[PDB]
Image (cartoon, rainbow, N blue to C red; front, side, top):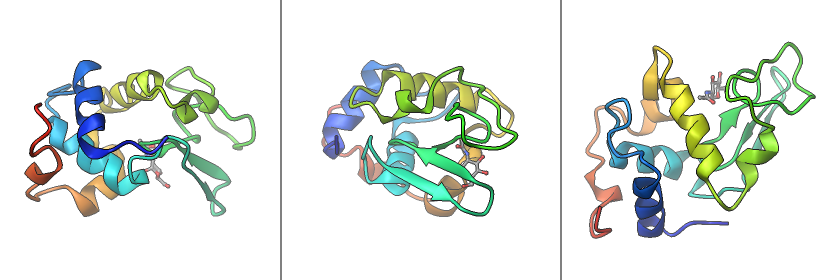
Length: 130
Ligand SMILES: CC(=O)N[C@@H]1[C@@H](O)[C@H](O)[C@@H](CO)O[C@@H]1O
């Protein structure tokens, strides 16, 4: 599914993402916008290293989920990458929380560094009631 902006903001809030490990909801929204356009079924194959990015946060198979076809990969979220393609984003959120329990935090997604870091991200949650 493709979420509408404020629908996603409230969904993420109910799932406990506002301020998780210090990360504001607006940062999570900025991440989802630029990774996938709020699209839970999005996939991106990385021919360079044979990994694939999955779902609304475009979480990568080399480290975070298992798809069986990524060489020398691990599965730190202990999920099938299929779980990151559901309309219900609970599992994707659990995995995103696992990602940011590691040292880099939200910087684990390079797109966040390029599109959200040191930026005014307040627009992504304006009007959503969060
Ligand atoms: C949290 C996460 O999935 N990070 C991955 C990152 O580790 C990877 O090296 C990069 C390359 O496509 O894609 C994503 O940013």
